[PDB]
Image: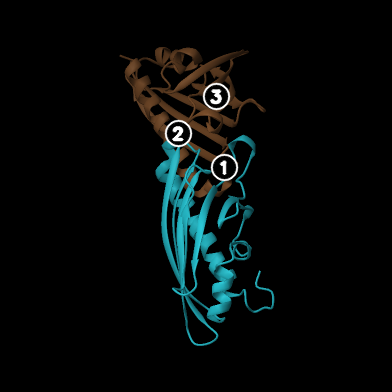
Chain colours: A cyan, B brown
């Protein structure tokens, strides 16, 4: 009853070598450990994963974002992309990481994601609600970026 | 998961006698006939009634304001009041009409209502959704005032 369309970009520099940063971001499970409020990340094999976010918030009126993506990593090109798996869940999500060395121990990273999320809330409330959902999604992504920036402090990168 | 607190007042003057105006306003079923988007009015007896408003939106995620009040009329005092019935529905509602004759064929009327409406939406949405619920509640009251004023013609 309400579909929310999101398109966003982030730029940041992660203070670790290109090889380390690429290897982390190319590893969906290890990367995902730094994403806030993930409930399940189902390994579907063949570079496909289903994301089930934590629900909000009460019994029959609760909502939950669920979506599946296929991932493609190209270390030579410094690009990792993901595209939506049709007919799975209530979100349609695509995105990418673009990376490049900044010296021997830092990496410039550009994040992009396009996401369409359909939630069962009253259509009458479309204009009031959509901004809040997008704002919350931007918050989650900001947190993800900050967690990733600190992932290499830090012997274990999960 | 979100509670919206409303408090409001309306003033109007109605070009009919005190007896006509008071008697319609004190007659809950007749008065209620003029309130918009009522799904049902339940006679709980003892001058109490449950209001069930039209829902929004659909299936298991729909929300619906439901509340019950006890009414008390005092024609000598020019006051009709309603008090909430605890435990009924998801709203707690109180209010009153205060009437004063402005000559033999005009009646001044003051409407007041306090309403606490608990809606089952994620609490994340409180700041955005509260003013929306309030806007709609005020729009309903405005339409009520206008319907009543026209019913006295």
Task: Indicate the secondary structure of the residue bearing disc 2.
Answer: helix
Q: Which mark is residue A100?
A: none
Q: Mark 3 highlights which residue?
A: B81
Residue projecting furthest to the front: A46
Identify the residue at horizontal 46%, vertical 64% (top origin). A96
Task: Indicate the secondary structure of the residue bearing disc 3.
Answer: strand
Q: Mark 2 highlights which residue?
A: B137
- Relative vertical location of residue A156 with respect to residue B88 in this rendering, above or below: below
Quarter assignment of residue A156: bottom right
State whether residue B149 appears in this view: yes
Separation of disc 1 and disc 3 at Cα?
A: 40 Å
* Circle 3 residues within 10 Å: few <14, some 14–19, many ≥20: some
* Circle 1 residues within 10 Å: few <14, some 14–19, many ≥20: many
Separation of disc 2 and disc 1 at Cα?
A: 26 Å
Percent position (x, y) of residue A72?
A: 49, 62
Percent position (x, y) of residue B142?
A: 38, 30
> Marks 2 and 1: same chain?
no
Q: Mark 1 highlights which residue?
A: A63
Indicate the chain on which mark 3 is placed: B
> Marks 3 and 2: same chain?
yes
Observer-side mark, 2 or 1, equals 1
Q: Quadrant of the N terminus of chain A?
A: top left
- Relative vertical location of residue A73 with respect to residue B81 in this rendering, above or below: below
Percent position (x, y) of residue A102?
A: 47, 84
* Circle 2 residues within 10 Å: few <14, some 14–19, many ≥20: some
Mark 3 or mark 2: name the one nearer the start of the chain: 3
B108 or B4: nearer the eye? B4
Identify the residue at horizontal 64%, vertical 37% (top origin). A59
């Amino acid at each position: 009853a309400i579909t929310v369309s999101i398109e966003l970009n982030r730029d940041l520099e992660i203070p670790a070598s290109y090889d380390e940063v690429f290897d982390l971001l190319a590893d969906v499970p290890k990367s995902a450990s730094h994403f806030p409020k993930v409930d399940k990340l189902v390994d579907l094999g063949n570079n496909a994963y289903r994301w089930e976010m934590e629900k909000v918030g009460v019994d029959k009126h609760a909502i939950q974002s669920v979506y599946a993506c296929t991932y493609h990593a190209d270390k030579e090109a410094g690009k990792i992309t993901w595209s939506p798996i049709k007919g799975e869940g209530n979100g349609v999500v695509s995105g990418s990481w673009t990376l490049s060395a900044k010296g021997d121990n830092a990496t410039a990273v550009k994040f992009q994601t396009s996401a369409e999320l359909t939630v069962p809330l009253p259509s009458l409330l479309k204009l009031a609600i959509s901004p809040v959902i997008k704002h919350e999604f931007n918050s989650l992504v900001d947190t993800y970026m900050a967690n990733l920036k600190k992932a290499f402090l830090e012997h274990h990168h999960h």
